[PDB]
Amino acid sequence: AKFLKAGKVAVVVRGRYAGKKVVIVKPHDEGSKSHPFGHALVAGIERYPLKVTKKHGAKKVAKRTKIKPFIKVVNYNHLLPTRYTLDVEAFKSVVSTETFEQPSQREEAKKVVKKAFEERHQAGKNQWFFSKLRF
Amino acid sequence: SINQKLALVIKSGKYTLGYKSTVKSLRQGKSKLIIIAANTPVLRKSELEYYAMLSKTKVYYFQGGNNELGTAVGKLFRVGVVSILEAGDSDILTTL
Amino acid sequence: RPRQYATVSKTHKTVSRAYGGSRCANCVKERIIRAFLIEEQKIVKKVVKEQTEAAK
Amino acid sequence: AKRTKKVGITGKYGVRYGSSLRRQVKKLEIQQHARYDCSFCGKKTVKRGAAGIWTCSCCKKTVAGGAYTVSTAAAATVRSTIRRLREMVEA
Amino acid sequence: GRVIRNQRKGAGSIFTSHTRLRQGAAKLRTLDYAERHGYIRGIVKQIVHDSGRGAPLAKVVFRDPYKYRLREEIFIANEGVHTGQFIYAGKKASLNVGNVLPLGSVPEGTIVSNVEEKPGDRGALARASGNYVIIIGHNPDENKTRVRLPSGAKKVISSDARGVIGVIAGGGRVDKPLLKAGRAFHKYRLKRNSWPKTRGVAMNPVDHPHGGGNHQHIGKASTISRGAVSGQKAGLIAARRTGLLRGSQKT
Amino acid sequence: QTLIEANVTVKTSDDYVLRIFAIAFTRKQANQVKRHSYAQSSHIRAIRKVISEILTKEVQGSTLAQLTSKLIPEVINKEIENATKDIFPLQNIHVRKVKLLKQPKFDVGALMALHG
Amino acid sequence: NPLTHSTPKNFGIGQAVQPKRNLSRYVKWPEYVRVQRQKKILSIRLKVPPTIAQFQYTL
RNA sequence: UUACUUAUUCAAUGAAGCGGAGCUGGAAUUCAUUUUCCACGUUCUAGCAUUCAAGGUCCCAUUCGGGGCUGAUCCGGGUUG
């Protein structure tokens, strides 16, 4: 009956990324070394894309379709799970506990996640995930 | 009566008391029944409903406040929500 | 005092979270949860209305 | 501990104002200074700020209610009456 | 031989109301489109004590249907209305305590308060603490509603007049004896300059029609005609009857 | 002998509600040598509940004209007797006054239907 | 095309801010405009003597 | 007493939804189908709702953008009582 899968979509409600839609990709339910709690490795969107209309010719379109992601180790209690699910293949390999604690490949994984998120947003899919939570 | 079922569950099976514990149980998938008091705040009640929908567990609404739910569950404090993990001897999961 | 706030930099007047210098963490969390849950409630109510209209 | 036989809270008034007036004031003063259950959280935390203002400090809520009681008998009667009328209109 | 207390009160220099600490006029929202064609949902956000008034007031917030902004209204709080609560104002609102349904919308026997005398005057009847107006009946043709007023009175008013359903909060206040000239002093020092009152028989004949005499007596009958003029209307004005009552209100 | 009186407030599909009475008695059965033959005061409850159920079921799905046309032939008392024979024969269980508590609009079209 | 979506707001009684419609019917006109229109209205609403209605009979 | 409103009087509103007819359906079930009525997208939650609005459609002398109609029915300028 577990529903904290390695590919699900939640919203972070605590921390600097409060109210931000993220995809849980690596669930560490049975603790860890530096985080002996029930937590998860997730990849959210720090800056949502702006709405796109027929009245911009490709340039404002690219500017408003730019995506700025983030990766985070976050507690389950600070996570609010949602029924939506995101595909995790392009960055599951690049997101792991070893990629954390070290900013160089932290930014590298951020680049990979950014490329994947931009591709998946220009593709007309996962619009709820790529939309913005208003509160 | 439902109070008798709850007392039998207390005596026989396993349960957790409180919102934090019951949310933990719903996330870990070991909770089967979630009893929510009538006077539980609507935001908390809807959050528990969403968690139960996600984890495919059954939700029962106790017609009574947290004081009455604590009295039924046998403790002398307020419980706003209880989680039933195994009934032990009652048929509370099979009923209703 | 307000003029000291004017002369003080932005970091001390706010927190990095959304609604940083205006609302507390608990209130922000409660309103985020309320927003998401009420939107989900609205979606399921909309599909229920659609299906019952289609049936009738 | 019973320090006074029958004056209760009206020992502050001592001897003045008359026994009957002091008794009425006593009944209403215990009513207004009592602690009441909060229908939303279930804790005995509802105090009175002013007449008709009843604040629950634990859950940070305010309720409109009687001058010396959280809910008057008239308020309960009109609650029942409007509930009955609403149910009749609905069904 | 000199102007009397009520004559001075009418001029009203020191007899005006002390309105510094009042929280604004307690009126219902305007009847523009939504209150007469549907309902608008507002949040009662805060419940406060209005100084000089025995009933609490409610700071409520609605959304402006025409421009992006919030509109704050000062309602008279009904009993049971709590903070952060959805109240609903309009023709199609549900019969719940705190809602602002019109009289034509509420059914027979309903208990309403702060009811409008005419549609759009934002509340005129049953506004004091613990008071309410009962719906006695409806006349759909020439749409009208017969209601009972806290004075035990019958008034027939337009069915489009609104009123918040329930009873004014802060009831039973007058049940407590004031017990002290100090309590009366504070009450009236926040209300207006009308206390303490000296008795006309205690004043001098220059100061009052009741003044003068070697004994403190009124002298003439204390029932005054309705056609009497200013300075003469002291005592009982146009008293139909007089003396201790024995019976009921005949209603 | 014991009297049993019952009343129901059955809701009508024609936007009416019919308040209906029912009157029954216990009677000296054959082979009886007793003088009173009183019921056990719980039989009375059982007869009251069965009468209420049967009246409600019969009135439900019926209009005023159908109700009158089935009340006139005096078959309802025999139907009640048939349905409650098991506890007692129970003859003369007649169905007392029915009255409408409110009515819909003036129903000019219903008048044309009745007079056409 | 895959980036844009169907927003439409609902303009119900308490749904969303009403759109900027034509309020030319409800313009609080200047006083002289009001005198103009109401003077015409009064002239056509009163029973004019035949000298009017032999005028206003332009060829 | 009668079917009046324009004089006059009263009260509000940033003079915003007035009157009438139409889009859609539910009715007695229509003695032939606007003939009579109604509704004209919101009630478990102290969330949000604002860039001549997104979409749709036609036209683009085509730069980092637009124009008309629509979305948001039409007529009468009596702001409403």
Image (cartoon, coloured by chain):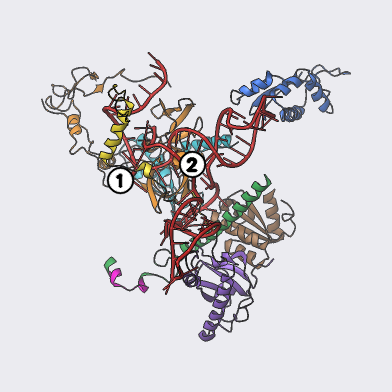
Chain colours: A purple, B brown, C green, D cyan, E orange, F blue, G yellow, H red
In the rendered view, would you say D58 is above or below E27? below
Residue occupying the point 31% across, 23% down:
G47
**Mark 1: few/some/many CA within 10 Å (<14, 14-19, 20+):** some
Query: E109 or H2: which is nearer to us?
Result: H2
Q: Nearer the viewer, mark 2 or mark 1?
A: 2
Callouts 2 and 1 close, C-beta under 8 Å:
no
- Position of E227 with respect to E91 (left or right) is left
Tell which circle, 2 or 1, labels the residue nearer the N-terminal end. 1
Residue D42 appears in the picture as rendered: no
Check if mark 2 and mark 1 are on a common chain.
yes
- Position of E213 with respect to A105 (left or right) is left
Identify which amino acid the numbered label 1 is placed on.
Arg
* Residue denoted by label 2: E38
* First to last magenta residue range: C4-12
In the rendered view, would you say D3 is above or below H63? above
Chain of residue at mark 2: E
Residue occupying the point 38% across, 69% down:
C14
Residue E173 in which image quadrant:
top left
What percent of the width, then of the height, locates residue G5?
55, 61
What percent of the width, then of the height, locates residue E24?
32, 45
- Position of F79 with respect to G32 (left or right) is right
Identify which amino acid the numbered label 2 is placed on.
Gly
Question: Does the magenta portion include C54?
Answer: no
Residue F26 in which image quadrant:
top right
Query: D35 or E172: which is nearer to us?
Result: E172
* Residue denoted by label 1: E22
